[PDB]
Length: 74
Length: 50
Image 1 (cartoon, rainbow over the protein chains, first blue to last red):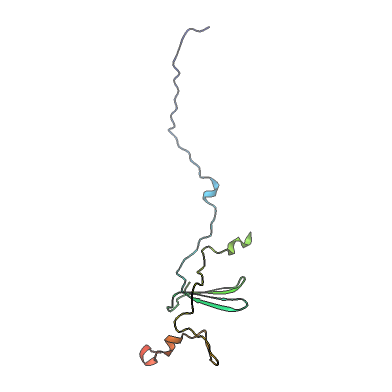
Image 2: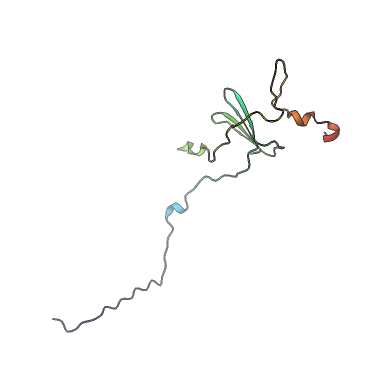
């Protein structure tokens, strides 16, 4: 039987906060140092030189993977 | 892939245009170094220094 009619209180208080980072926030990426390329030399069958900026080059990279390439002041 | 590392991160500079100022370009008989800077070696040691 029913004796009464009432209004339904509830305590919805969130007072605690637990947020956990999903895994992919910590995954790696590939980051690189970046300087302005002053020049480039490519050689595979035939050598080719491109010069963007002529200055005394303070750093030089050599990379052999497919074609021989030399990145000047890179 | 293990190779996914060796991709280019940035777009590499295109070759749009002609050989640079005082480039080595070789006529009928010319002894040409790609290596030696044409303009900065010709410039007197007296001035530029050793």
